[PDB]
Length: 129
Ligand SMILES: [Cl-]
Ligand SMILES: [Cl-]
Ligand SMILES: [Cl-]
Ligand SMILES: [Tb+3]
Image (cartoon, rainbow, N blue to C red; front, side):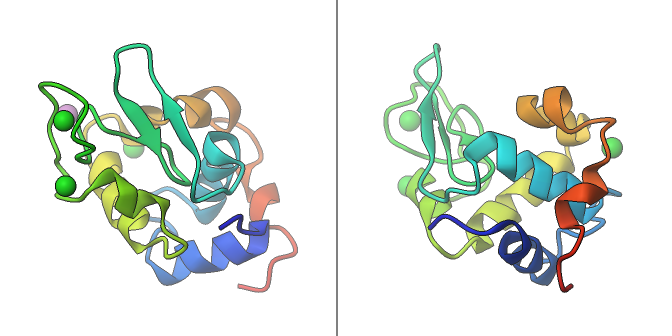
């Protein structure tokens, strides 16, 4: 599923991401924009053999099991395929675990390089929320 901007903001808000670990909704929508272009089916293979999955490009090295990332962990206790669903629940629950680690949203390279420090509220501007 390719969400619309305001559609994703509303789904994230319902799933409790808004102000989760002090990160306003605009930060999450901005991160999704640059990680996946709002596409739940987005996948990207990394140089180390791990793969990033879903709207927030969550990595198999630590967070989900895909069966082909040797020596990896599955800290969200899910198959990586669950992160590709039209239903964003698994991606949101897993993102909450990631952002609770010591690095916050800097875990998302696109957020650090393209959202961090910007007017992230522009990403939820005009949305009925
Ligand atoms: Cl594996
Ligand atoms: Cl699994
Ligand atoms: Cl933080
Ligand atoms: Tb850690």
